[PDB]
Image (cartoon, rainbow over all chains, first blue to last red; front, side):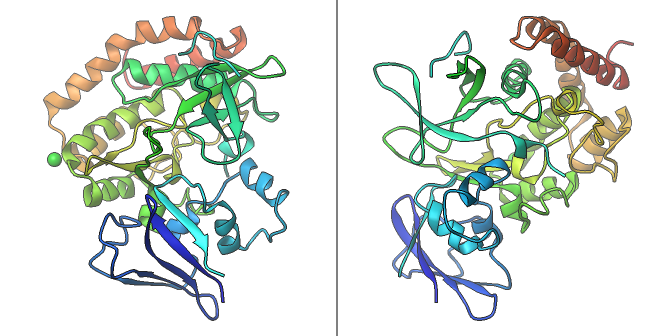
Length: 102
Length: 267
Ligand SMILES: [Cl-]
């Protein structure tokens, strides 16, 4: 289905994967060795599973009025957190950037 | 544009626009992406938010809190707009790791209020480089927010920054007197302290919070409490000179006096 590159300060760090049902999975690239994507995701583990949208990537989405500004600029559903993340992935608060693979 | 002599949810009614600082003109340019500043124009729901956030930010700098470059500009409708320099952008188009406490504790936008000040301490102990140093300003930041009526300090308003491989609490952001901005304000604190969001007392901040949860000694607490005592005169002087309206200024001073009296600042 939908997958996306996850880069840290320009350097590709891993892949965030939308998984079957409603789960999500982030996998670190073996080559990557800089700083962690999130402090909740140390490099000592390369695979992280989630039953919902992971909270770090959800924390990069707009809020309040700026979320309504996004939903009226793009043709995207108000609950599609992964889809909204791809639309803003080029610039969010952290040093992390997301670009879709498809 | 250009600045002038300024060199449940509440925040979800004000815009947070990205902007670059023009090199020659010195004016701001709102952009969709790749901005180095955040601009907050007037809100059509709650009044005088930019002027509120501007003076509150300066009050935090007076008590010794780390505050980035902030100020006020003139919008195109000749209203005042608050600006702040992002600390996750540091020239040469480089970035710094910035994570808020909802991301660090497994919460989201819908549950950013379902936490507590005790969980905020747990995050700092787990990730910060010098947790003992961070507790000192968390005590100062929590006391400051209680004094200036900032009742919107949810999980997304606390952030950890990674600068020079040192992990500490980010500089101040989204600090304003949100009690005077609304009517029928429900809480004094956004996250409960000792299971309390209202009617917090001196023993809640100086004994349970400062001693039992943060581990600060008595001489450290006395020095910080004394710091807030000497800043009350300058705080009232800065507010009277701020860009708030006279009616908004009186609501700010009255609430500041009420919180100071609760902490026995005048006796
Ligand atoms: Cl320490």
